[PDB]
Image (spheres, grey):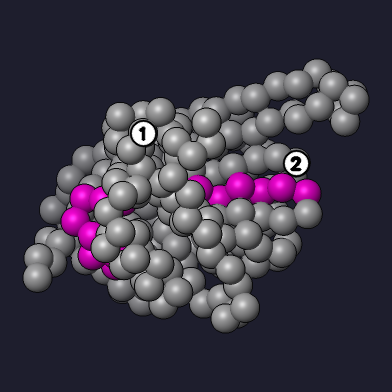
């Protein structure tokens, strides 16, 4: 679990890794539809983060329909969570082979407090699919245009992506 | 304006990556076998 240790470098928040997988079809796979999400663990320092991250496969090497989620401790990676329900996310769709580096850059910027939006960040997701990967960063208030504008600028600055790459913002409710 | 108390850039994060660690016990679950290295 997460403890603050004098010899270690604290993060501004504790964060929790999550892992989900979806067996997407009844015809598509021989097995029946199945969906699972499991909390991996929670960490409080830079050194503790590396203990977890260095022992996880990079997302570009996951198979099937799988996701890593990295969210502030106490925020579930589900839009209906209190911390998320009035929020939204920046979405970046990537051709296969780019997600592992972009995920690392994203979560290092998030954990390191590089966004400068106070408490607005909820967490980040990398979703591995068959023909593309999707990376997103979620924030608390979807209607806070100044916040969501600052996140975009930091993303463009820290992610190291071709300037042709599109980014889209989506408010979680808009899905209903 | 208001800087966070604990701030690290990318290079600072990598600088603290200790090369001798122990896998957290939270990861030692059969469910995570596909994702362990």
> Residue A64 — which label?
2
Tell which residue pokes out farthest to the bottom in this image.
Answer: A163
- Residue B3: give x, y in percent of width and height: 13, 67
Using residue A92 as the reference point, say whether residue A82 is left or right of it.
left
Q: Residue at x 54, y 44 (%)?
A: A68
Q: Which residues are magenta?
A: A113-130
Q: Chain of mark 1?
A: A
The answer to whether tags 1 and 2 share a subunit is yes
**Residues marked 1 and 2 touching at CB (< 8 Å):** no
Count how many numbered circles sit on residues in the image: 2
Q: Residue at x 34, y 48 (%)?
A: A142
Mark closer to the observer (1, 2): 1
**A73 or B15, which lies in front?**
A73
Q: Position of residue A65 (x, y in %)?
A: 70, 40
Mark 2 Cα-neighbour bin, 10 Å: few <14, some 14–19, many ≥20: few
A119 part of magenta stretch: yes
Taking the spot 31% from the left edge, 50% from the top edge, the residue there is: A143
Q: Is residue A8 something one can see in this rendering?
A: no
Which residue is under mark 1? A85
Please state which of residues B37 and A112 is positioned toward the viewer in this rendering.
Answer: A112
Q: Is residue A65 left or right of residue B2?
A: right
Asked if residue A153 shows in the view, the reply is yes
In the image, A6: left or right of A35?
left
């Amino acid at each position: 679990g997460p403890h603050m240790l004098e010899a270690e470098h604290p993060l501004q928040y504790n964060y929790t890794f999550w892992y989900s997988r979806r067996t997407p079809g009844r015809p598509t796979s021989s097995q029946s539809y199945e969906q699972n999400i499991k909390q991996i663990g929670t960490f409080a320092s830079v050194e503790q983060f590396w203990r977890f991250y260095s022992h996880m496969v990079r997302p570009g090497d996951l198979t099937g329909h799988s996701d890593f989620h990295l969210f502030k401790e106490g925020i579930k990676p589900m839009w209906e969570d209190d911390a998320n329900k009035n929020g939204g996310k920046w979405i970046i769709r990537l051709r296969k082979g780019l997600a592992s580096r972009c995920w690392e850059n994203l979560i290092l910027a998030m954990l390191g407090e590089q966004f400068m939006v106070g408490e607005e960040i909820c967490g980040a997701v990398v979703s591995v699919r068959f023909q593309e990967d999707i990376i997103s960063i979620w924030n608390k208030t979807a209607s806070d245009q100044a916040t969501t504008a600052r996140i975009r600028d930091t993303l463009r600055r820290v992610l190291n992506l071709p300037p042709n790459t599109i980014m889209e913002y989506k408010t979680h409710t808009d899905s209903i | 304006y208001k800087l966070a108390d604990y701030r690290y850039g990318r290079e600072e994060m990598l600088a603290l990556f200790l090369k001798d660690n122990k896998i957290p016990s939270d990861l030692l679950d059969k469910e995570f076998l596909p994702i362990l290295q």
